[PDB]
Image (tube, rainbow over the protein chains, first blue to last red):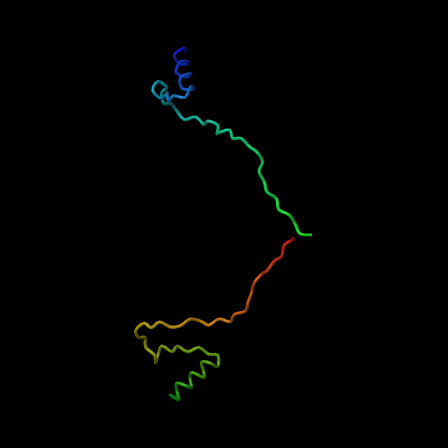
Length: 49
Length: 49
């Protein structure tokens, strides 16, 4: 666990780690999608009198 | 010529004639196109100022 934390911190520092090396491939799992940010954007026109 | 004018008048009277009988096909010739009747059609909307 300590070693895993070690390269976890190393990766989060900004370095590249290939976790496929010790994490094995397994069956399919339906992961949730990306969580997007949202600011409402809209343009409305004007009308003649 | 007279007989040709005769069934030409008959055809223009409203009936249909298969003129392929006395007029066999020949080599290709580039013909003009249909002449349309043209009137100006357009929309010119307005807007506020």
